[PDB]
Length: 186
Length: 186
Ligand SMILES: Cc1cc(N)c2ccccc2[n+]1CCCCCCCCCC[n+]1c(C)cc(N)c2ccccc21
Image (tube, rainbow over all chains, first blue to last red; front, side, top):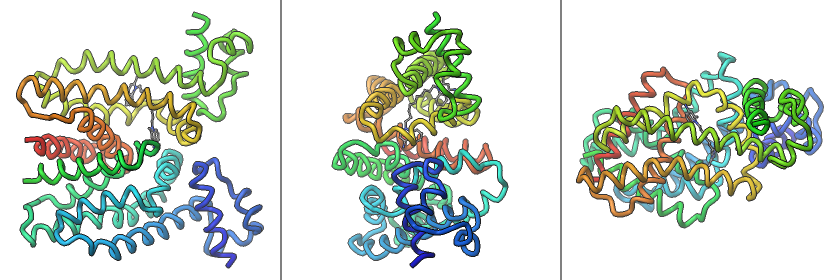
């Protein structure tokens, strides 16, 4: 598939290299596609990017739901999600690329556009977990939406800023975090 | 000095045109130095940059030493340091060159190694706050080294992946997080 070929080489390079490091030229030489290809469903570069992001976001959200069963209580769901957040092959491996992409477009107003609906899925997982926990009486969070955002970002941090040290060490930290966070919620 | 002069000019250059565009040539001519002297001092642009980064870490620490006086108890220092981390990077010029540099050299262990020694220094702050916090019964943490790395990275998370939100909101979420976290240690 050509339309689904660009997306392939793209995600690949955006991960190995940064947002800038990888260029349209490089994709075209490994995916074979003139300017045209990139225009109907692939306008700009930040377009082909915001695309990949959504795909991955869904790939992750899906995997999460197909695996959250191994967790009976929401307290366990919180812990798990965070741990999985470290093992996955979806979305998280593009955080560095995102950090860049943002530090180099936070001017073009059409940024907080997708950067919005995207920030939703990103925190939705926590939103449910937290609200459901309220119903299930595991805790009582009145500012769910906030805690959701905080948890989501703190976790992204532990996943992103320690991406080079022993995976077991990581898993250990993340769990000690999840333990400390939930415990500060009541 | 002439070394100090290269670092100076280099910091500015990096700040004005980023890491990738700054050429050692520019650095050499503007610092009124020479390819040879610049080689003898840093060997490479990457090292030159890491060196600036080190000096920068120093200023940060020194600054934090003055600023933490406004914080009597360790609980307070935790709160302060976090907010500070968020607000100061909002308008930290080098930030862009750093993002660029990291998301382009974390592949190499040579460089990644040195960078971790740097990130460590950041973490030390939290280690001190937590250790002292123990000795004052503000809390009881027996795995300081861990809690420290965790805090550190969670905070980097909230600082990095939120940029796109009203500055106050960001500060609010941060302070909330410091509240939740600090409470889950009791
Ligand atoms: C003076 C001074 C003054 C201030 N007001 C100040 C304010 C805020 C922060 C530093 C400040 N400093 C000095 C700051 C010196 C900082 C040296 C930092 C070295 C480390 C970066 C590590 N890193 C890692 C590990 C992993 C990542 N995925 C990653 C992704 C994107 C970007 C960086 C990444």
